[PDB]
Amino acid sequence: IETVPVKLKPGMDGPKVKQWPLTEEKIKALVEICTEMEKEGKISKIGPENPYNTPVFAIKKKDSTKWRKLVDFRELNKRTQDFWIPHPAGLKKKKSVTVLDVGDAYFSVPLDEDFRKYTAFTIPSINNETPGIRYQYNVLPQGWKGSPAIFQSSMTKILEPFKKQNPDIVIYQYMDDLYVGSDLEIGQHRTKIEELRQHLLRWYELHPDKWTVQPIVLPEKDSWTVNDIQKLVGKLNWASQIYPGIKVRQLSKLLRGTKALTEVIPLTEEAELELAENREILKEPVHGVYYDPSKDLIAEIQKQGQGQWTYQIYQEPFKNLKTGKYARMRGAHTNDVKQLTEAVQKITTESIVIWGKTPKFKLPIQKETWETWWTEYWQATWIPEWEFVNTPPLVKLWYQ
Amino acid sequence: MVPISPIETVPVKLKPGMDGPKVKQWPLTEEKIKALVEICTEMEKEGKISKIGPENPYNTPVFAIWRKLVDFRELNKRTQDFWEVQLGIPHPAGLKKKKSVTVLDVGDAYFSVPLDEDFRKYTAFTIPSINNETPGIRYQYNVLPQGWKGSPAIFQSSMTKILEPFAAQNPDIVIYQYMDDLYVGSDLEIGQHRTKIEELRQHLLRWGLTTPDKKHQKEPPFLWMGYELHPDKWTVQPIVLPEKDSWTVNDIQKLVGKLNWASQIYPGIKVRQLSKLLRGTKALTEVIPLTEEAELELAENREILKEPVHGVYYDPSKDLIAEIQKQGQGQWTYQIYQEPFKNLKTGKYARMRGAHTNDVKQLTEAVQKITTESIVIWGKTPKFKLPIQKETWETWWTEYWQATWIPEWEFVNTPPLVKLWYQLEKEPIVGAETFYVDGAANRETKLGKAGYVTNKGRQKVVPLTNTTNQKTELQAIYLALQDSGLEVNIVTDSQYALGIIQAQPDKSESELVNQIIEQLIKKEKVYLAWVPAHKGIGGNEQVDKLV
Ligand SMILES: Cc1c(Oc2ccccc2OCCn2ccc(=O)[nH]c2=O)cc(N(C)C(=O)CF)c2ccc(C#N)cc12
């Protein structure tokens, strides 16, 4: 009911990002949505004196037939002043966590006057026929980093009774999402979630406990071919960058001679001992692996085929903070890009739960394909940063 | 007098920290001064400008050619940024056929849009007096000046706000605004159309804006931005390829301009060689001889540009189709249409700069480009007709290490067909010979060696001059492919060679890589295995090639 002064970082102008082209149905959806919001005062039309712009598009969330408006506030977010809570390290340790969309509440708090001009967006026209419908926000916009920071006091006031009632439930907030972690039963968790949503009304099943870090495993065979031993030596040589005491000379001793790749080679005793020592070394965690809140998180994804994808989250090379394997199949059996987009969304969610920020992705896809199609399968309210790797990494099969 | 509705002004500021312009007035001849005094007296009588005292410290030079021309370049430098009047120009293929299209001249509305009063003081200008024996006449603008930075954007936004209720209450017509001209189309009967045109003239007159009762000068075919717009079709303005005995650089840039511009409706235009002659020149007057490939290409262009070809307008009730053909040397051509033989538009796509490539990647890129262009122009993705078998694409994207996707498409049997030229095995081949390859070079003398040893005792080492490590590694693999049967296992330690071959190219800048490709095409089964170097892996003989 009272505006809080918001400004930009010193020396930085507002965002001026080109609006990318949209299909006719998304344009119509944005026209309806923005017409309704204008009737509700949440947005207002602007004139040509506003040169700032932020891209906008439309999506359809899970289990819904209504269009939703998504605003790519990335540039404005990195250009918005830093607002100033330690991350709940117990949220990832909880048995279950539920994600709630609390974005509507932001629309009840007005936005600072002089700052509104920086939230300008454009509904584009087909074939550049009309100049495009320009709007700016009058309330807290969903997707902007200042919206959860400004609403933090009100959110604390609304959640104070529920927090005082259940001290065993962990509550976290990130952008327009509220993460509620507990250890109850799925039915008790769903009834509790309905209790919290009706508690918030009058004012996504996720299980981190079923997630762990994945170690480097070696094959267990009774007969080894020349090729099997060569791949084993390659994988152990790669692992020696991560683990110090990895030793391969006794196994490479077996590859002496020019033998056919499919020829079975029996392991000497020294080779078995070396392999066993290497297994024992790989059973231990990596030495000196810590998280640094001042550094970026990097997430790499490899396409393993058959709907299987591997990923690693790290900050320094060979110092993995998280590793995982997303093989879920949800209506994307014939579309690589949809699978990759869902994978990026899940990894970003896990990164939000663990560290409270999004990572920078290295996507195994051409820039033009990704930038052409990723908005068709996006369902999250946030958007991470990403880059594109064009050379096939050798380590792919070493994560398979 | 009928009360005229006022046009809401746009608040305009200068750039932060900057001040208004203060430029010295150009000295003018007596006749020019008299002409500007007459013109500015008439304009002041009309209300476009107003006299100001000496308190105004700003000044902008004025000229006459009469016709008054104010040079606002400095004030433009000091004026705030505005939202772009047009993010892009429309494309004719996106337009929708109309029974009637009328053109209204709203040029008189340009000087009728008021300027923000707090900003008018920055538009001050001085008319020099005769012999400079009196103070020059001081004026300032009360409306949007022609040449000022924000005049087109403010004018277009004001006109849009004025036209909004009329367009809303008349959905059965279409109104477009381009510069000082309105364009009103409809499928109504011609009488109803002229009626609603009169209604628009009245609605605009309710803001004091006058549209000429005179018959407008623009009439079919409309010539606009190098386009010809007809009642039922569109095309490009006539493209004439000149007959030149010798071609300079500007002649080749004008020819590639005419060919690039003509490629949007004339199918099959190629610009590879003619633009290749302009590679790394940076000299406008340099005369460059014409290669034979540029001669054949230019002759094919003259054969395609023989007779006029037209495009149709968009019918949203029909499906949108885009068909692609490969032309070789990284050239691709495509047609976008809804009915056979009748194109909406055409175009081409040239491969990006790269060391290695294959046809499937280039086709994918072309499809992405066509998708983006179609969404721009028509707001939807077209259904594709591609020269590639379904099984080929399935094998490619299922086995490719990157994520890839093309939208809904069907196979069309129009050679040359995009195909996979070789496929590496996933597992070692039983019964096939195993070639352990290696190569090495000296960094100073550039002397190297490449070779292999096999499980059957076959061996070879070849010495090489003026080579690198990477080159000798590729050369080793090439030797293994040369001297092996139809099925072969190859073991290398070159992460470089494996990085090249796992990218699956069918063409390369390096002739050695192309030779390797030609060898792989001839094989039945090839398994390529990698091992770490210098790890004592026998068979992998680093010492045999470092001698
Ligand atoms: C005639 C015209 C435009 O045409 C139409 C105006 C209104 C409705 C539909 C229309 O086109 C349908 C197709 N069509 C086309 C021609 C025809 O004769 N009959 C037809 O049915 C559109 C334009 N552009 C690109 C704009 O941006 C206008 F703001 C023009 C730009 C410059 C000039 C000139 N000099 C003429 C333009």
Image: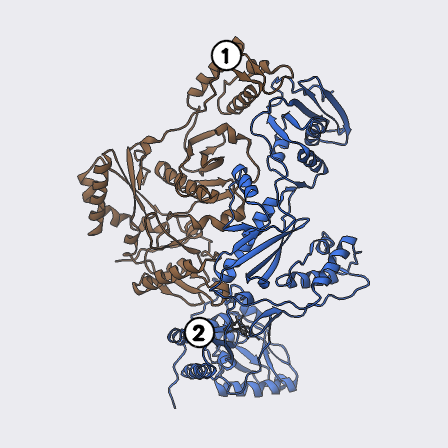
Chain colours: A brown, B blue
Residue B18 at least partly seen: no
Tell me which residue sits at (64%, 84%) in the image. Answer: B32
Tell me which residue sits at (56%, 59%) in the image. Answer: B336
CB atoms of marks 2 and 1 within 8 Å: no
Q: Which mark is residue A200?
A: none
**Cα distance in 3D space between marks 2 and 1:** 83 Å
Q: Residues within 10 Å of mark 2 (few under 14, many from 20)?
A: some
Q: What is the x, y in percent for residue A145?
A: 37, 49
Q: In the rendered image, which residue does mark 1 sit on? A: A272
Task: Count up the numbered dots.
Answer: 2
Q: What is the x, y in percent for residue B186?
A: 46, 76
| Residue nearest the viewer, comparing B527 with A294 | B527
Q: Does B187 appear above or below B475?
A: below
Q: Does B515 appear above or below A80?
A: above
Q: Is residue A39 left or right of residue A25?
A: left
Are discs 2 and 1 both within one chain?
Answer: no
Q: Amino acid at mark 1?
A: Glu
Q: In the rendered image, which residue does mark 2 sit on? A: B158
Tell me which residue sits at (59%, 23%) in the image. Answer: B532
**Quarter of the image with the C terminus of chain B in it:** top right
Q: Amino acid at mark 2?
A: Ser
Q: Secondary structure at mark 1?
A: helix
| Residue nearest the viewer, comparing A133 with A160 | A133
| Residue nearest the viewer, comparing B189 with B238 | B189
**Quarter of the image with the N terminus of chain B in it:** bottom left
Q: Secondary structure at mark 2?
A: helix
Residue A37 at least partly seen: yes
